[PDB]
Length: 77
Length: 77
Length: 150
Length: 150
Image (cartoon, rainbow over all chains, first blue to last red; front, side, top):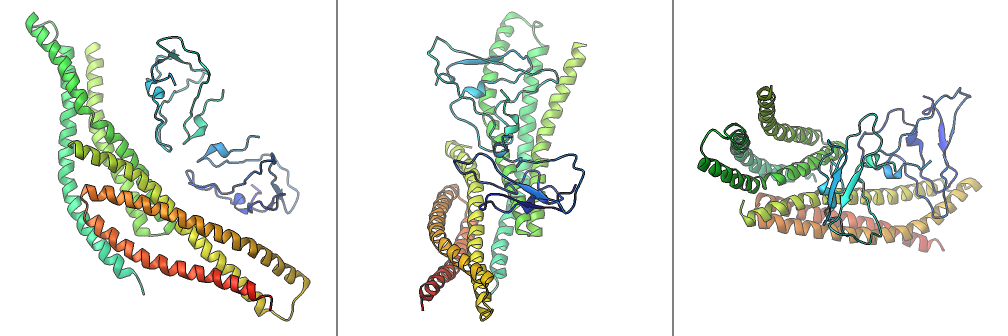
């Protein structure tokens, strides 16, 4: 996994910083809150998250873990 | 609402009694167990609930509430 | 200043109350295990009389035992009306205990975190052990059924 | 037990659930007030650092200070609104604790009553002091912003 070595940024200026998403250890299985939360504006339909790596990497898989406590907030696509 | 006056049944002989689903009062928000649970066989894809009413009624809307604690058990379609 | 002395006498009163409560709950757990075993044995004995002793006696006792089955079923439902709340109160106890464990881990009180973790574990063990006696009796009933059928 | 005792146990279940909710809301309120105070303190500390580094004003740090002042006006209105809403939520939590205490006093718990009274007086002193400190913090911030003209 190369996520910890990278820096994650978002296009929307109001987005809460998401460096917590890159922790090498997963959060609590039944944690009562989400590690990173984004609030959609009524006119907005897509969220932006860019991860920049120190060097080129032969990427194979991307793993995204939604906030399992409330899966209603899992991204649609 | 005409669900409480009806009788619910399923075509799966191993299904739990679903009469708890027709009450007007929903259960606790974060109850560890859903009000009614169905165990899917590895080859089975559809389970059916057949509500029968005492007399014909002019049906307008159907409301189904999944288990808000764990949306992962919400039916796909 | 430090609220250590305030916490000290507050928890001194709390510990005296909970020591009295622990003795009272030892007595009440003796009472509860006795009552639970009696209820489970009443259920299984009425099932045994329902299944094992039909047709051996005469017609008047047949009608008598049928009316006994009906009345005892009604009275058992009435008495078992108390057990439905036990499941929900154990649900809320488990939820509160898990919350206490999480909150004590968050605050960092090691003694309180250990207390809450052992609290959820101990209530789980106690309720699961009375239910384990009940389900041991139920498993014995099922084994007696499968051996009696075959 | 009896009908009154059955009502007591039902309201005990209900009040235990609502007290789980109340503990969650109260801990959230305490953490929110802590974040309130620490954000105000951090902003004041940054302002004090900028004033301690006076004389070497540059475009970068002065633009940062301008952004801090704009965000400080936004923070002033947000802090006032959230102070209002946190006071309202604390009043709601106090009412929930009031109904829980009514249920407990109708139950008959006295050690819980005296512990709750001691906790109430201690936290009354504590919240009075901390809220006075906070309100003084925003009062001083507003006064400094007002006197920034001269």
